[PDB]
Amino acid sequence: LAAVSVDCSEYPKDACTLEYRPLCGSDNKTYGNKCNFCNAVVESNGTLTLSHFGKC
Image (tube, rainbow, N blue to C red; front, top):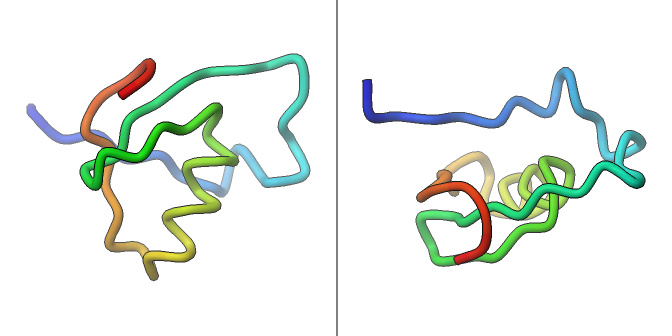
């Protein structure tokens, strides 16, 4: 289907190192990883979504 979701249950903010992965939020936010995305998502209250992968 056409719907993605990054769970911060498998990738905690305490789990973000050499592993770098750019993402794009529905708000047009440029993330650097799932932690960065979950970080913003948390700030959204869980409303922020993932527009796509890579850089916005």
